[PDB]
Amino acid sequence: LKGVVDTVLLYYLKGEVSKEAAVAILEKILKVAKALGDEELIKHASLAIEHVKMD
Amino acid sequence: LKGVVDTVLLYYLKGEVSKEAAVAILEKILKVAKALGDEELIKHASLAIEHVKMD
Ligand SMILES: [Zn+2]
Ligand SMILES: [Zn+2]
Image (cartoon, rainbow over all chains, first blue to last red; front, side, top):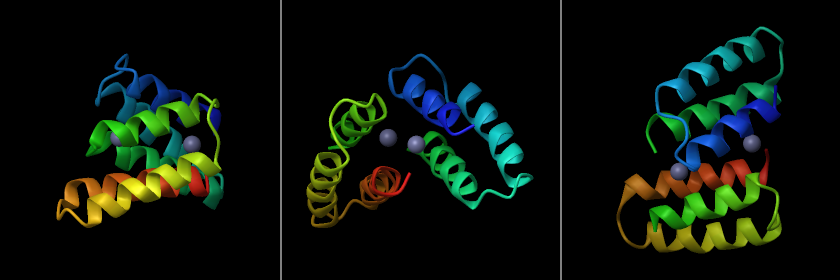
Protein backbone atom coordinates (compact mmCIF):
# COMPACT_ATOMS: atom_id res chain seq x y z
CA LEU A 1 0.00 0.00 0.00
CA LYS A 2 3.10 2.18 -0.27
CA GLY A 3 3.59 1.65 -3.99
CA VAL A 4 -0.07 2.52 -4.54
CA VAL A 5 0.45 6.02 -3.14
CA ASP A 6 3.40 6.59 -5.46
CA THR A 7 1.41 5.12 -8.37
CA VAL A 8 -1.45 7.57 -7.78
CA LEU A 9 0.97 10.48 -7.38
CA LEU A 10 2.91 9.54 -10.52
CA TYR A 11 -0.27 9.14 -12.57
CA TYR A 12 -1.49 12.50 -11.28
CA LEU A 13 1.72 14.35 -12.16
CA LYS A 14 1.50 13.08 -15.75
CA GLY A 15 -2.05 14.45 -16.03
CA GLU A 16 -3.89 11.12 -16.34
CA VAL A 17 -5.83 11.32 -13.05
CA SER A 18 -7.77 14.26 -11.63
CA LYS A 19 -7.87 15.97 -8.25
CA GLU A 20 -11.06 13.97 -7.57
CA ALA A 21 -10.19 10.35 -8.30
CA ALA A 22 -6.71 10.72 -6.81
CA VAL A 23 -7.90 12.25 -3.54
CA ALA A 24 -10.65 9.63 -3.23
CA ILE A 25 -8.18 6.76 -3.64
CA LEU A 26 -5.63 8.39 -1.33
CA GLU A 27 -8.17 8.96 1.45
CA LYS A 28 -9.28 5.35 1.10
CA ILE A 29 -5.64 4.27 1.47
CA LEU A 30 -5.06 6.61 4.41
CA LYS A 31 -8.13 5.03 6.03
CA VAL A 32 -6.54 1.61 5.49
CA ALA A 33 -3.15 2.82 6.78
CA LYS A 34 -4.53 4.57 9.87
CA ALA A 35 -6.39 1.41 10.96
CA LEU A 36 -3.22 -0.65 10.44
CA GLY A 37 -1.03 1.36 12.83
CA ASP A 38 1.68 2.39 10.37
CA GLU A 39 3.02 5.84 11.16
CA GLU A 40 5.30 5.47 8.12
CA LEU A 41 2.27 5.09 5.83
CA ILE A 42 -0.04 7.50 7.65
CA LYS A 43 2.45 10.27 6.87
CA HIS A 44 3.17 8.99 3.35
CA ALA A 45 -0.53 9.08 2.45
CA SER A 46 -0.87 12.41 4.26
CA LEU A 47 1.90 13.97 2.16
CA ALA A 48 0.38 12.60 -1.04
CA ILE A 49 -3.04 13.92 0.00
CA GLU A 50 -1.63 17.39 0.72
CA HIS A 51 0.15 17.42 -2.64
CA VAL A 52 -2.93 16.35 -4.62
CA LYS A 53 -5.39 18.52 -2.66
CA MET A 54 -3.79 21.96 -2.84
CA ASP A 55 -0.59 21.88 -4.89
CA LEU B 1 9.49 27.26 -10.43
CA LYS B 2 6.35 25.24 -9.73
CA GLY B 3 6.94 22.88 -12.64
CA VAL B 4 10.55 22.30 -11.58
CA VAL B 5 9.44 20.74 -8.28
CA ASP B 6 6.94 18.51 -10.08
CA THR B 7 9.61 17.52 -12.63
CA VAL B 8 12.03 16.53 -9.86
CA LEU B 9 9.32 14.60 -8.02
CA LEU B 10 8.12 12.90 -11.21
CA TYR B 11 11.67 11.85 -12.11
CA TYR B 12 12.23 10.58 -8.57
CA LEU B 13 9.05 8.48 -8.29
CA LYS B 14 9.86 7.09 -11.73
CA GLY B 15 13.11 6.00 -10.06
CA GLU B 16 15.59 7.37 -12.57
CA VAL B 17 17.55 10.27 -11.06
CA SER B 18 18.65 9.86 -7.42
CA LYS B 19 17.71 10.60 -3.84
CA GLU B 20 20.73 12.86 -3.26
CA ALA B 21 20.41 14.85 -6.49
CA ALA B 22 16.67 15.36 -6.05
CA VAL B 23 17.06 16.68 -2.50
CA ALA B 24 19.91 18.98 -3.58
CA ILE B 25 17.92 20.50 -6.45
CA LEU B 26 14.83 20.83 -4.28
CA GLU B 27 16.75 22.61 -1.51
CA LYS B 28 18.04 25.03 -4.14
CA ILE B 29 14.47 25.60 -5.36
CA LEU B 30 13.18 26.00 -1.80
CA LYS B 31 15.91 28.59 -1.15
CA VAL B 32 14.82 30.55 -4.22
CA ALA B 33 11.16 30.21 -3.16
CA LYS B 34 11.83 31.38 0.41
CA ALA B 35 13.86 34.31 -0.97
CA LEU B 36 10.99 35.28 -3.28
CA GLY B 37 8.11 35.72 -0.85
CA ASP B 38 5.58 33.28 -2.34
CA GLU B 39 4.31 30.94 0.37
CA GLU B 40 2.31 29.04 -2.26
CA LEU B 41 5.57 27.47 -3.48
CA ILE B 42 7.52 27.49 -0.21
CA LYS B 43 5.22 24.72 1.02
CA HIS B 44 5.19 23.00 -2.37
CA ALA B 45 8.98 22.66 -2.30
CA SER B 46 8.87 21.76 1.40
CA LEU B 47 6.40 18.93 0.71
CA ALA B 48 8.54 17.61 -2.14
CA ILE B 49 11.58 17.77 0.16
CA GLU B 50 9.75 15.82 2.88
CA HIS B 51 8.73 13.19 0.32
CA VAL B 52 12.16 12.73 -1.26
CA LYS B 53 14.12 12.94 2.01
CA MET B 54 12.13 10.44 4.07
CA ASP B 55 9.54 8.51 2.06
ZN1 LIG C 1 6.26 8.25 -1.97
ZN1 LIG D 1 3.34 19.37 -7.10
